[PDB]
Amino acid sequence: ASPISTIQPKANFDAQQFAGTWLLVAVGSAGRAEATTLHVAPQGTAMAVSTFRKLDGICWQVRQLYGDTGVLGRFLLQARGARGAVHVVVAETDYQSFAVLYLERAGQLSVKLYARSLPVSDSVLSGFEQRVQEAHLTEDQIFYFPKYGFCEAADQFHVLDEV
């Protein structure tokens, strides 16, 4: 049924090795990109995820909980009430340099490439592109995010807790 159910999650996904900071490199989607950083922390079998984005010089933080859906590597971003549930799968990753995640919102699949640091190896970028094509998305539906202007901390007036 769901497009994401056909994607295989990382074999024996290990939240402990996936923990830490991840930088958003690009997103393949059919739906201004800000420098985005992810801070991941295991929480039981789920993962506490904070996302930091620099908006007009100001750093914003959003706290979310990637709930465990039973299959290792597959998570669920709670139907926030206002906006559908988001299914997430960590498909491929070596934990030490890159990670390819797939997201599904309202039956629509998207693919995101994350890196531990820049630059991303040519091999991984091509691999990501190969995966976007296979997901039936075009080269024009790939959005590259900023390689500068990242932020990883916000003050109390710019924190949105969705947990």
Image (cartoon, rainbow, N blue to C red):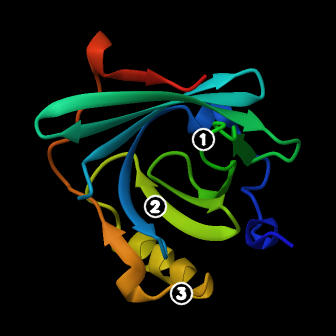
The residues tagged by marks 1 and 2 sit, at their Cα atoms, a distance apart of 26 Å
- Name the residue rendered at 60%, 41% in the picture: 82
Neighbourhood count class around disc 3 (C-alpha, 10 Å): few under 14, some 14–19, many 20 upward = some
Residue 144 placement (x, y as % from top left): 30, 67
Quadrant where the C terminus is found in the figure: top right
Name the residue tied to disc 3: 133
**Quarter of the rendering containing residue 125:** bottom left
The circle on residue 82 is 1
Mark 2 secondary-structure assignment: strand
Residue extending farthest to the top is: 156
Position of 58 compared to 63: left or right?
left
**Quarter of the rendering containing residue 136:** bottom right
The circle on residue 113 is 2
Residue extending farthest to the left is: 57
Q: Earlier in the sequence, mark 2 or mark 3?
A: 2
Q: Give amino acid for label 1.
A: Ala
Position of 146 compared to 74: left or right?
left
In front: label 1 or label 2: 1
In front: label 3 or label 1: 1
Neighbourhood count class around disc 2 (C-alpha, 10 Å): few under 14, some 14–19, many 20 upward = many
Q: Are marks 3 and 1 in contact (CB under 8 Å)?
A: no
- Name the residue rendered at 20%, 40% in the picture: 55
Neighbourhood count class around disc 1 (C-alpha, 10 Å): few under 14, some 14–19, many 20 upward = few
* Viewer-nearest residue: 49 or 114: 49
Residue 101 placement (x, y as % from top left): 58, 58
The residues tagged by marks 3 and 1 sit, at their Cα atoms, a distance apart of 31 Å
Residue 44 placement (x, y as % from top left): 76, 21
